[PDB]
Image 1: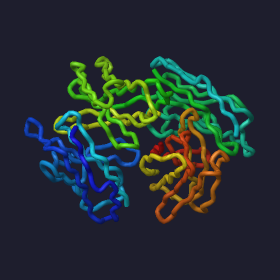
Image 2 (image 1 turned 135 degrees about the vertical axis):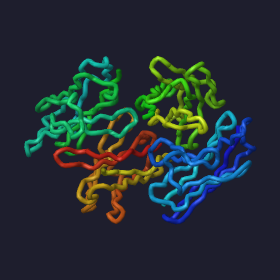
Image 3 (image 1 turned 180 degrees about the horizontal axis):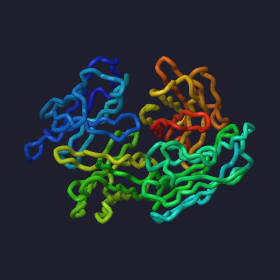
Image 4 (image 1 turned 135 degrees about the horizontal axis):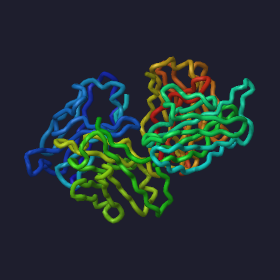
Length: 111
Length: 111
Length: 115
Length: 115
């Protein structure tokens, strides 16, 4: 099973100050087709987790421009231009190219 | 520290037929100011509890007319004439007349 | 509007089993995979398995293979996840989630608490 | 619209303590009482205590008065509840809810799961 390791595990960002979360897959994760199903999920306090980014860098529907994803092969990172109060929660990088799909440990970002 | 007792504890309802839930306080619950703070709350699947009825029979703003409460002194009853799918969840009566406020055990409604 | 509405919180004695329902609304049920993911405070989120509403095909995580069963009732557009032989570590919020095509979990149910 | 937003889920070890927050917005935080109610296994909902943001004055049910503590910060419109010396039986969803007056809990927090 592909293991995804995120760092930091805790990220208390001062409001307004930018941020970034690292994630490294234990193996190349591009599917047999050409797609790398590496995604980022945010679970805000007590809410169902929601999709932020897919295909490593494509932002999901109503997600703000503050978020963006980058990386390839081994390393991938999530980045928030200006962390706001409502951005708090546990961020998870996810890979669905290989069965079983796996999630990272989750990074808890706090103001 | 009044003991509120609801009956039944399980109430499978046939979509469309009326339903009813009883609640009896272990002692009179009308406040010295004359108001009987008897309330009913509904906790729909996975959501925070929400106010349905207060002052025994007053519907809270936004609550459909299908719901209604009645009773006096020590016996109270909620009525969901024509139960709908979104009515499933756990219902609770509650008294705020005496310190500490206390809730019934909860009646689970399912179709 | 697309939405997955799951069954209410469940309290279960150890050794017992629980069956969670997920009714899909606002879209065509059989066109997408329905996953089941759980959030147990110990280790974030973990994929439990999935099922294909059309053929009833399923894939289970190794961790849950011997005690989880997924099924679906296309007539009422509802998926089910039954976890048996419950233990303290199963206390968690269970979520069903539909696949959105280029992304794995498009819409999520509100989650079902099982203790 | 008023919003009562609580802190994220938490997992605790027996004997440990948990501090749950509840930030309010949309109304005048200091003019309404803030209560904490919990949804615990085979105990439905039970009142735990309350606090008046404006006066910081509190009240705690006896069942928890020897382990809980409620406080608030008017500069950030937030209330807190610490349940010390936790144990298995405390595994439950904790809620904060303001009271209206003629009625009680009109606005609820989304809840904070603690295992």
